[PDB]
Amino acid sequence: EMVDNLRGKSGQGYYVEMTVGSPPQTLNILVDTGSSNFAVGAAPHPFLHRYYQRQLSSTYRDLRKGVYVPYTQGKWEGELGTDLVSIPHGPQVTVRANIAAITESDKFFIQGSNWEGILGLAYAEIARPDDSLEPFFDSLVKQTHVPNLFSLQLCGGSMIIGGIDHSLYTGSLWYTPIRREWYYEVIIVRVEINGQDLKMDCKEYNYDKSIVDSGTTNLRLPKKVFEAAVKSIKAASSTEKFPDGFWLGEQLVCWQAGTTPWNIFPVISLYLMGEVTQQSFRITILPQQYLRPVEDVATSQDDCYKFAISQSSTGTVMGAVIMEGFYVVFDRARKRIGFAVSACHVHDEFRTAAVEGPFVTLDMEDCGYNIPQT
Ligand SMILES: CCNc1cc(C(=O)N[C@@H](Cc2ccccc2)[C@H](O)CNC2CCCCC2)cc(N2CCCC2=O)c1
Image (cartoon, rainbow, N blue to C red; front, side, top):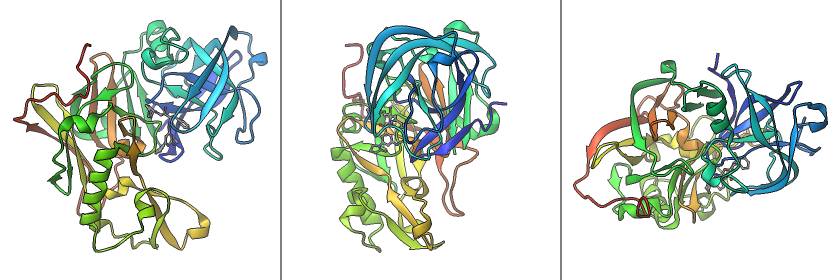
């Protein structure tokens, strides 16, 4: 009953149905593993079809404190409070949770996204105002018997709370350690394009950090890694020349409907640290993931795409376009992230997204940018 409980797309986010308040107010809530605040629109907004009305809830408690939350894209401010929350197509339970009632926002809500709030699924360490504001999933685990784990299959898609659904993946689950519990931080040990090593000190791949983030669209890469990746992808696809603006994500590339030359674009392999010393596994990303379709009836004689790899000064972000086609297990209980090939991964009759291992590295350097436990 939890299968197919997500809707949405990489560009505007994936959301799940929730209720807040007594009596229950149903709202669509974006699932975001890249933040830790539960917040809902709570005042009229041009892009909102509905919003949380605290005056209709007898169980609302005002915490008499404001909160401001900035993201890479968008920001909002609101009033902190608590109320009863349920997930109709998740575990059948009710918990009292912190909720930020958004009263002001800028470039946060997305027109036509069909969601009205956001569910930050990361750890308290990064919650605003501070780590004393318990995140929703922490409250869920504390107040119910739900196992301390959830999994995401982004396609629609599924969020499985408290469990792993075998019907959602094929092959083996490979686990990489959560390096630190704030974001879902992981360690990349190697990057290949077209099978060719980028040949950097592996700490570069994780400067300042690397995270798994369902709330960000793109694969975002540290400047140095991004520039190396673009040069390698350019070289692989050199039979066609694109304007520099495409590579900057500032303009579309279009082909006649159905003629997209997938074969000229390379596969990208990200090797993630394994659970055992000097072992790793890789997840492989097809161009169907990193060239993101942009729907627009005006351009619809063509298929058009944005380049969904982009530069970051805040570390690697493995966003939705990476997570799509994988089943990703956020195993908080065992401090690890699991990857397997998704039942809904898109591909062609030549190449397939993969999760595979084990691979060994002879270089013993810690690929984490920061010294652990300091
Ligand atoms: C789904 C909408 N598309 C996005 C969203 C975000 C973004 O900032 N997402 C937030 C959540 C959010 C969700 C929906 C609307 C606003 C915010 C996440 O917490 C960041 N997590 C952070 C990321 C970095 C700091 C640490 C964790 C960045 C995008 N960008 C920016 C350029 C490339 C790209 O894809 C595209």
